[PDB]
Length: 129
Image 1 (cartoon, rainbow, N blue to C red):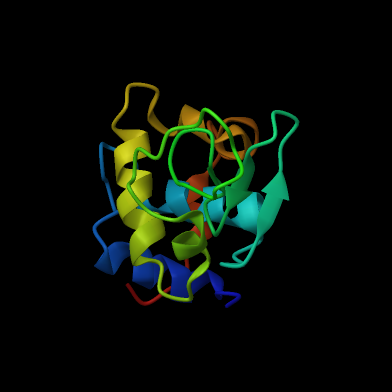
Image 2 (image 1 turned 60 degrees about the vertical axis):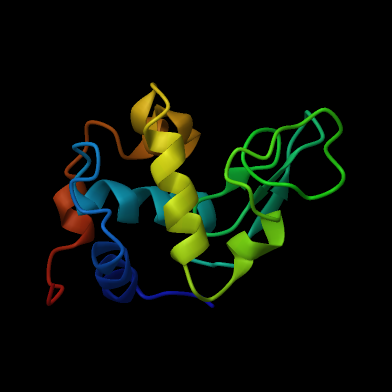
């Protein structure tokens, strides 16, 4: 499923991401825009053999099992395919673990490079939240 901007913001707010670990909703919408273009089915293979999955491009090296990333961990205790669902619950629950692990949203390269330090509230303006 390809989310609309405000549709995703409302879904993320419902799932508790607004101000989660101090990150306002616009941060999460911005990260999703640039990681996956709001597409829950996005996958991208990395140069380390891991793959990034879903709307927040969560990586199989650490966070989910895809059966083809040898020596990897599965810290969210989910198959990576669960991260491609139209239901974003699994992605959000896993993202909450990632953002809590010490480095905040710097875990998402696109957030660091394209959202951090910008007017991220723009990503939720005009939405009825």
